[PDB]
Length: 276
Length: 276
Ligand SMILES: [Co+2]
Ligand SMILES: [Co+2]
Ligand SMILES: [Fe+3]
Ligand SMILES: [Fe+3]
Image (cartoon, rainbow over all chains, first blue to last red; front, side, top):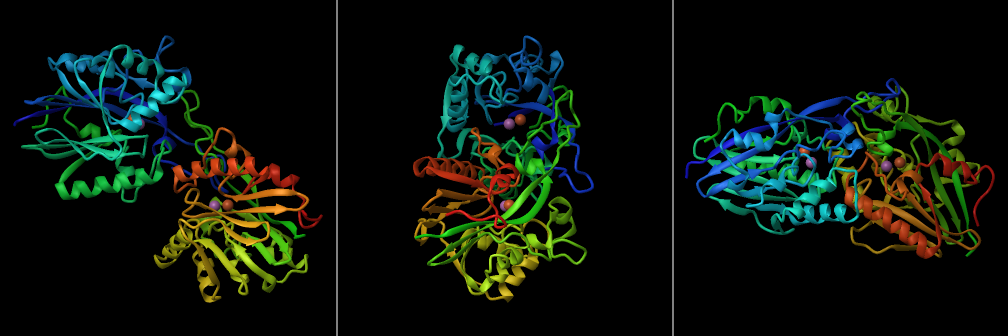
């Protein structure tokens, strides 16, 4: 099999650095009112155009996320603003590749945060692969009518109204062979309730691990590991990072982080080409 | 049957509020360089003068902690400075109660952080009860010559040279009946590797739970729970806080937080009296 892997630029987001690197600049006797920064980071998706079928990793943010009539609560827009041009929208990025939503066989949701699950509702002909604990956690946010937070009620509303077809990865489920050289990695709890990664083995490029928010950046990866402020299971997070490190060394694979500005710049995006 | 419980003022410490309440004030589009604060909080120990023997909960900081020739590293001194008058020193606080180190039968170390295990070395005639995981973790810090962070090399050095007698609480060990109405609570991992609390049943005052850093403050306690930045096991931390809440409700016990300025102000300290 000779697949093509595309990195699609789905805009940028800004947030408190402390979210990304917990306690990045601690206050001191000499700096008692220490300042944080408001850092920019990429929101990207990955399309594996595979002969067995098209696989999508993450879905970025929903077009109608930001704004006065935005699905995102105002507090969320102010803490995690998403800047993107129309071309950065997933549906347009796919269109520029002559890929219709209906052509996606599999969507892998690393987690159900606002900036990874925004456009799940588009893929009504796909099987949405998600960690059961992540699914459960988001569904509770919905049921309890939680309007703030990283789980967008209106996005979840849409998933349900659009009758998405789900395939939950069970807590103790082995990695899933989705297609030749494409494995869903079950990272479990850490950054969120349930994280999924991808291991892709390309004939030419070789091995790629899509870590998503299991590893925000290279600063996160280290060594040493510098965990995020947005974390559900600190222990599981630490374990997941080391697990990823071990797999990378054993499979001689690259590790693609979730939101690393520097790494993203070096990527070949969908406007220039792909990875074989 | 008729004991007296003393609260001993062992000084004040300042640190970044983000340590106490994580992400207490996140940056926004309108406040991108959001400032943290450098808050003050109490360091205290608890003496249970019990007919079966004297029980000490926590040991505060070592007198030789701060300063150019201080045991604490400068970075630590600058991030977590301890201010204390001679009288605030535990040795002095005990002397004013006509209690010699040698008279302590049991020292319960909630955890082995610098602000709780400073003066363990004094109690050479006591049994030091500590969580095995906390003990293990600190001994690793020592063995690896970790000089910075919350585990003071020189402090641990002194514990070993002074030949302290340890009694480790095993990971899955039940609560320990230390004396009539005195009971060691095995909280396990959370704030640190292994946390111990006390439940004291006082004839007059009733039930008291000593939570130490299992719960920093009333703000931590909520509801809802607002976890700290100094955390090892987020899940365990959350579980512990809720376990304490339950025990408190079922035993109609007060919950004494580790570092709550407001609550401490209301405590009757060793200079004014005791709790029966
Ligand atoms: Co996320
Ligand atoms: Co502590
Ligand atoms: Fe993300
Ligand atoms: Fe403390």
